[PDB]
Image (spheres, coloured by chain):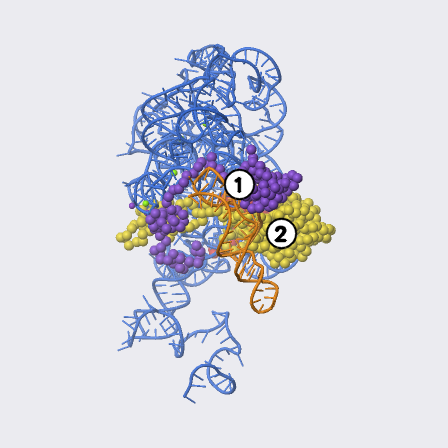
Chain colours: A purple, B yellow, C red, D orange, E blue
Amino acid sequence: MDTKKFRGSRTCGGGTHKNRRGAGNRGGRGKAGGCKHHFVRAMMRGYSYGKHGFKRPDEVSRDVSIVNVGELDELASYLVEEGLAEVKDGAYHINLENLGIEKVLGSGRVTKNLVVTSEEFSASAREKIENAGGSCIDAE
Amino acid sequence: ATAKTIDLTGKAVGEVELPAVFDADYRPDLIKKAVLAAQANRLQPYGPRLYSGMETSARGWGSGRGVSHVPRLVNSSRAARVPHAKGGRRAHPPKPEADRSEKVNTKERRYAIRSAIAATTDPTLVSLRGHIFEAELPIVAVNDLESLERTKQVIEFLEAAGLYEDVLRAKYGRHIRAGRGKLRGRKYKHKKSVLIVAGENTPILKAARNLSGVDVVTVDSLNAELLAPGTHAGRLTVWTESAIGKLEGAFQ
Amino acid sequence: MIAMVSKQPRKQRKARYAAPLHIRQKFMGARLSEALTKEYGTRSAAVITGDTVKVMRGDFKGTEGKVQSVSLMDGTITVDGVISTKVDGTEVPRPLNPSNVMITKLEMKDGRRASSIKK
RNA sequence: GGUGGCAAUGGCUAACCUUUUAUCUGGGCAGCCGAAGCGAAAGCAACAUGUGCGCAGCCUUUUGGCGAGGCACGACGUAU
RNA sequence: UUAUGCUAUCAGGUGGAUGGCUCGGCUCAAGAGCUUAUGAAGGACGUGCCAAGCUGCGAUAAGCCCGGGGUAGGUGCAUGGAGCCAAUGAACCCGGGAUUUCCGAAUGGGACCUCUCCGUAGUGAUCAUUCAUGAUCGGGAACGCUCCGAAUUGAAACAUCUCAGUAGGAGCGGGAAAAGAAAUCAAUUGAGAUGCCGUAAGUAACGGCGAGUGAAACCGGCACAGUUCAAACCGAAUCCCUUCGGGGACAUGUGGUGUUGUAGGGCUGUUCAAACGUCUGGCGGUAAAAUCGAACUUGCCUGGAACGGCAGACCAUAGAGUGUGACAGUCACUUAGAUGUACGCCAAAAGACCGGAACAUGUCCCUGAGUACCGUGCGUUGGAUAUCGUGCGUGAAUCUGGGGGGCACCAACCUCCAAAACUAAAUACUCCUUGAGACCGAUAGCGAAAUAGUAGGGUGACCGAACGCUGAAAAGUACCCCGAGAAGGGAGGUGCAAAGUGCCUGAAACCUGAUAGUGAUGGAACGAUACGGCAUGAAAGGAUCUCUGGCAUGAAGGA
Ligand SMILES: [K+]
Ligand SMILES: [K+]
Ligand SMILES: [K+]
Ligand SMILES: [K+]
Ligand SMILES: [Mg+2]
Ligand SMILES: [Mg+2]
Ligand SMILES: [Mg+2]
Ligand SMILES: [Mg+2]
Ligand SMILES: [Mg+2]
Ligand SMILES: [Mg+2]
Ligand SMILES: [Mg+2]
């Protein structure tokens, strides 16, 4: 706190001088009392008692990097000028493997001919790419 | 935009196009941040020893003796160890484990450096900063200033450029400061006069080194605190041709 | 001798205060006269008991005399004619700092003195 | 929170190297946060705006119009 | 003359604040890093011409000898007397020696005896070797390794948990230590010793699933380094001591070979030729005290004294700083920059030496046991049926082999080869050295600005202070008077100034006196406000300001 502003206040913003003694003025140390007197506070701060679900091992579980077809479509020219994609007879050839993405999702619009090769596609990504005139290629 | 270059006699003998570092807007707030961060990163840990005032076995007498409940020596009534006891520990002293370093992002530190470099071109900022000079800013010197090896040659160049008055101001303005700094080793309060920036390591570093208030550095070793001593921009600086050439993408 | 290793006043004064005797010899240096500096190649030499010096600072500026005595611990010399008359009236020498005087004639009864002054 | 740098083609680097004696300059993409959520998990995976009201501001015949942000819907992803 | 008192100021005393100064402290960084039976550290006692403490030294005793550096003085903290030493080169510093009492690992025996007994003169204890000899012991600020191991506390009680493998203990031990060359980590296919740092991440995991506790791998860096045995085959082909005669070890195996995973090695045959390493060598670097190092001590003024002011003259690869009678680039030491250096340390050219690497063939040989594993108990761990340890019990296999891949087993795939050994660097620490500092500035900063772990306190384990400062120079007050005076006072001196020795400045409380006001008929939060008496009102405050009136305009109000 601003120590200088409280020089002369005696209690220094604490109320009574009998405040500010120990953990008794906080109701205990840490997040104690979450079943008894900090029960509602535990609900508010998310520390309510209980267990839920199970964790799978990190060595089998995996998350996939994603990119929506709108993001690919409306910055594909930047990808070609940066080298990560090429234009073959007018069709953008994007390989998500060198982008670090493994699943194409279907959010957005596809306005150009995208020939996209990726480890996985959502169904909607499939229709949006194929209706734009392009195709989807799985990574063997 | 463009700046004239003066030979060692002080006469303009050509033109140089100033890099984009020189048309950067004036940002005293960012300059202040950069200089304060560098000063803080220079600082040194300090504090009392680990158990200073606390290496006693003093314990309280308790109630029933007509005395305060402070800890006392086991074989005397002399109070010990408490911050309001004589010889007791300092409550809340400086800690050697305290971290005084400040971070400034490299982008905004470079922005501050560019702002301070552009501030060396404004006559109003430089004269308001304290400097005495009669030249036309910015001062770009031909590269032969870098090859001169004696202080007398630097004096002749600075006099031909109308900059030596600032050096004399720094020399005669050197004053013994007030207070405890003299005993700690900061006997004088020094002034800053002239910044010479060279293209690379040359004899002009040693040659101009001993001038009073003068800093001579290269473009690589150029930072915010040299260009804005005390967080104030507007340092009177002499750039060389090589320095201006080497400043094209220096902080952008 | 105190290098630029330490620019701190405390270390400088500690070095001077606890200087060994062979270092306190160099503290007795004094400026040589123009003739002596020309004919020795050095700017200064240690004041020795016997050589003639001219006092150039203090209450006795301009006096020329021979060094009567040198104290290495005090870093003072005693010069003929530089005295303090005391309440008895007897005349007592007033010690001088060697940096306040100038050597005008060297005592060269010691064959080692020439190399002592330089090299 | 106030003040700033940069900004989805994002931000910042950590250790460390460069110190020519702690600053500093230039490097350093490892990593972290943001960028997609929902689900215990398997897994699957969304609007670059479809509509309305309407503040500021602008235009205006001074009563209306357009209306970023805001508000209210509609639609969609996923769990149940 | 109102006493005893009260209030304010002043003078003085007491006191030691404040200010200024500081050879001390503290913190951080960079270095450097073991020592002792050839008797250490530590302690006791002694040691000085006058010497009590501390410091140094040891009956040769604030010291002795030699070489180098230094050179004219020296005789510690600590300028007193009287001497002594020193140009036969002292003092001092660097290197190397000598002396070195008693106790102490203490070690011929014994210690409420720092001494004492035998004197056969001293290898005390435990060990290795042939029995010549050798090793170990104690100490070291922290750091390191091994083992033993609480409670307060938190959970708002408390028991698992936490505190915490903390505190504390025992052993070992070096400049570092430990670890260390996969029976590894991965995952569909990869990497490739260890340590340390960053991150993963407060994630996985544990948990009255409460409070809390809590990784690793991958990845980015620092620094990089690999190898030696046991065995197969050979069989004394070896190693050690030595008085150089010989002696000891050794067939229960010295030595050679060999050293490992898509196996390696041996044995048989063929080919290529020999890399790493050890020793010598000292080009040259590092390297003692230390040496040299520019340029003013010019005029006037002020002053006790210029480093100041005003003129003038200069140096700068040197304007870091400190000292010097006040502020110094040019007075001194320095600095920047160059030199030199005994013993040492690293060290390239060039020589001497054991030797290295591929392939073919395989009813061939070898490849670590109370071990790995498992059962059960306990500790520990994030380790969860899936941490590590170790108590008890049980207990394999041998390349057609064995282990691992987070419950067990089966199968597939991937991966390695334990139960033997060593191994630089990167890392840690701070007794010590150097440097630095938005650190402290004498009730602070270390307890200690050190006659400080001291005085002093405690039977003991142990607890533990206070104390800095004359002045430029002692010029440290002559002579005289009083006084019992080697006290003190007066007078008189010194000094710019008494600053007159625990002496710079010199606050307040407190005490003595003086001055102003008041005061022996008087009522108490010691004041605020208004008006008066007395005193003061030099500076720093007013001068159409103060006093006293007139005139004009005058709000609210209004006789
Ligand atoms: K509690
Ligand atoms: K309780
Ligand atoms: K002087
Ligand atoms: K000075
Ligand atoms: Mg030991
Ligand atoms: Mg509790
Ligand atoms: Mg090992
Ligand atoms: Mg734990
Ligand atoms: Mg200098
Ligand atoms: Mg103290
Ligand atoms: Mg202290």
Give me the residue at 40% from left, 50% from top.
A44
Where's the N terminus of chain A, which quadrant? bottom left
Identify the residue position indicated by label 1 in the image: A122
Q: Secondary structure at mark 2?
A: helix
Residues behind callouts 2 and 1 on a single chain = no
Q: Position of residue E420 (x, y in %)?
A: 43, 23
Q: Mark 1 belongs to which subunit? A: A
The amino acid beneath tag 2 is Ile
Give me the residue at 54% from left, 38% from top.
A120
The amino acid beneath tag 1 is Ser
Q: Position of residue E300 (x, y in %)?
A: 62, 60
Q: Can the viewer see residue C96 in this picture? A: no
Identify the residue position indicated by label 2 in the image: B117
Judge from the rendering whether residue A94 lies leftward or rightward of residue C20; answer left or right.
right
Q: Mark 2 belongs to which subunit? A: B
- Figure check: D80 above or below E97: below
Q: Secondary structure at mark 1?
A: loop
Q: Position of residue C100 (x, y in %)?
A: 57, 51
Where's the C terminus of chain A, which quadrant? top right
Judge from the rendering whether residue A96 lies leftward or rightward of residue E409; answer left or right.
right
Q: Position of residue B17 (x, y in %)?
A: 69, 50
Q: Is mark 1 within 8 Å of ligand 8?
A: no
